[PDB]
Length: 178
Ligand SMILES: C[C@H](C[C@@H](C[C@H](C[C@@H](C[C@@H](CCN1CCCC1=O)N1CCCC1=O)N1CCCC1=O)N1CCCC1=O)N1CCCC1=O)N1CCCC1=O
Ligand SMILES: Nc1ncnc2c1ncn2CCNC(=O)c1nc(-c2ccccc2C(F)(F)F)[nH]c(=O)c1O
Ligand SMILES: [Mn+2]
Ligand SMILES: [Mn+2]
Image: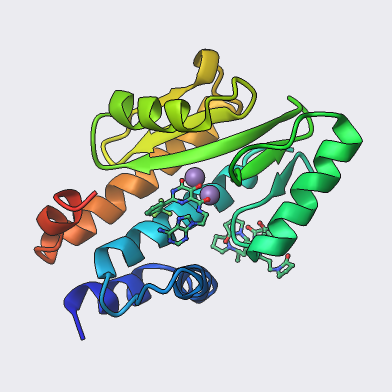
């Protein structure tokens, strides 16, 4: 039982922790062992949720659901809006901008992480939005979807999590593991 596991459980709302646990066990991974990946799965989950709570019924949340139902909704959006079915599961869908969104949270330079995912998805359709634990962000065609206030809020949350890890001497392992 690690210090990181107890921190994760005390730092994040219980629904987020359980969803992160479910996702990992779906891929055979143990939150009790891969504890830095545990914290990461939760942050990304929280960021996605804060992101969806930043617009007006504007976004359809795709992250958090089980694989099959996530794809079911993706197909239903694709066969309603016309948009082609993504190669990989996205994180949200914008009914206002009419595009899927891939959210990223990284401990490295925002450029590197965006480039990796863009080359990964290849399709010019799914919109990419990267956040860092230092408050930078980078989004496709410089289009950041939400208003600055809701996005700055996410960056503040990420930096508070980073400081909380540091005070507990867990940050260096977390950063040195992505
Ligand atoms: C107190 C308040 C609570 C948050 C909760 C919300 C997370 C998310 C909840 C679940 C619903 C579960 N299932 C099971 C299957 C069908 C289904 O839907 N999932 C996961 C998959 C998508 C989804 O819907 N929901 C519910 C409503 C919309 C939403 O996104 N959110 C959004 C902000 C961060 C967060 O946690 N709510 C409730 C509405 C307003 C709000 O903020 N919190 C917690 C801390 C911050 C905060 O404000
Ligand atoms: N290794 C895995 N473990 C559980 N589930 C996995 C999964 N790979 C795929 N899936 C299912 C669908 N995954 C996603 O959608 C998704 N995964 C990530 C990611 C990837 C690797 C390590 C940590 C992360 C995370 F950022 F969460 F912490 N980042 C995203 O931005 C994102 O959208
Ligand atoms: Mn995802
Ligand atoms: Mn993502």
